[PDB]
Image (cartoon, rainbow, N blue to C red; front, side):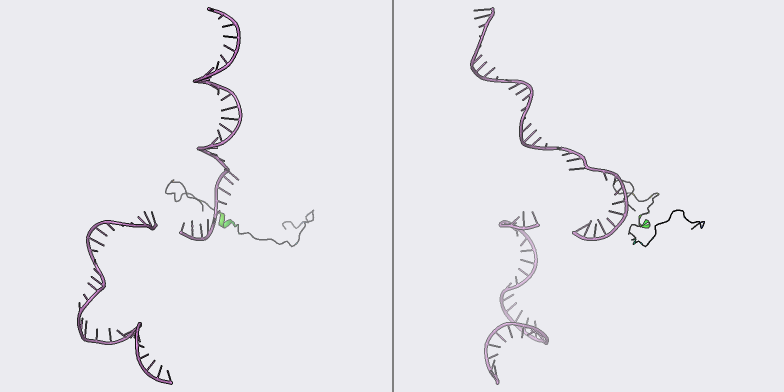
Length: 48
DNA sequence: GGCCCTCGCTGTCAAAATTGCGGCTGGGTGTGACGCCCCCACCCCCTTTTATAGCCCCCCTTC
């Protein structure tokens, strides 16, 4: 697709059924500089 | 004093059972939630009356 040259090997290509899973990167990304702390431990809380 | 045996006691090794402890790292959703029996104060209803009226039980009457 970039240079327009033929690929020397011959790619195996065809229609295949794919599924998108609920495991999505926007539901998983998580960061924390400084936030709320626990009532008992005074340590950072559990989970995003 | 010295040789030889059986015996009782504390003791020991061994077998057997009894018991405190452990069981990966981390992450993301969601969902939901005492009683028994007695004793002691205090209050309500028992009764009388009446006005008042809607409601309802009881007995009578109809066919």
